Image (cartoon, rainbow over all chains, first blue to last red):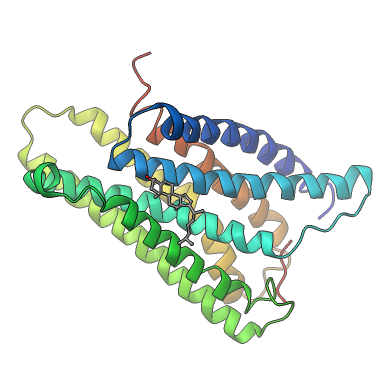
Length: 263
Length: 5
Ligand SMILES: CC(C)CCC[C@@H](C)[C@H]1CC[C@H]2[C@@H]3CC=C4C[C@@H](O)CC[C@]4(C)[C@H]3CC[C@]12C
């Protein structure tokens, strides 16, 4: 657009810089300083995915501001949208596999303590990242972001396939959080119930209201509504603001609350 | 080629 979309661009550049410094601190602390468990492997991979996504959002911010003020008319390449899509899908799939591993920890505690393979988690991590590549480049080369051209009749099909993948990740996160909540609300003795309940509803509403809108508008709404050309300048900058709020408040919730809280 | 940017 013109000046109508300008203040979401400044908002995504403030929350993008906050997300870069948060995910940089989480990446440095879990890479080079602290001792890691399987959960720190999941938090580290989630911070890497959000670091890639917020890097590509802040360079989209910078090329839009270079288009507006300096009038350079720089063109970012088309594969940055592809690797940003891969970062977004991996950053949501880490949230789903965090909720699945917590459900397996509470429902099956003897197995999760004593018989869990220590090289499971990273293996699960790399397979989810592998599937992110299988949903990114097979997206992008059909949508013209790779190989300069592509059939849109296939591109819409692969957008619907990854939309089914996003609603599958949401029902896996919601079903696992529901199973963990009924397992604690039936059978808890010494657990901190209200803090655990509030953090579970916080992570579910972050995955619903913040992480999911950009994927639903980018892969699903844009093909099924068929008149979204005037709906763009309202729904798309607020969706990248909400997804950058998801990627920026994933270091603060999953690390600096779980593990940097007392200080 | 698709476009919403
Ligand atoms: C499937 C391949 C091609 C995609 C891999 C993407 C690359 C760039 C990165 C992003 C974050 C990385 C992970 C970050 C954390 C660790 C923990 C470490 O103890 C084992 C490797 C592992 C699990 C890395 C594996 C590779 C990884 C997933």
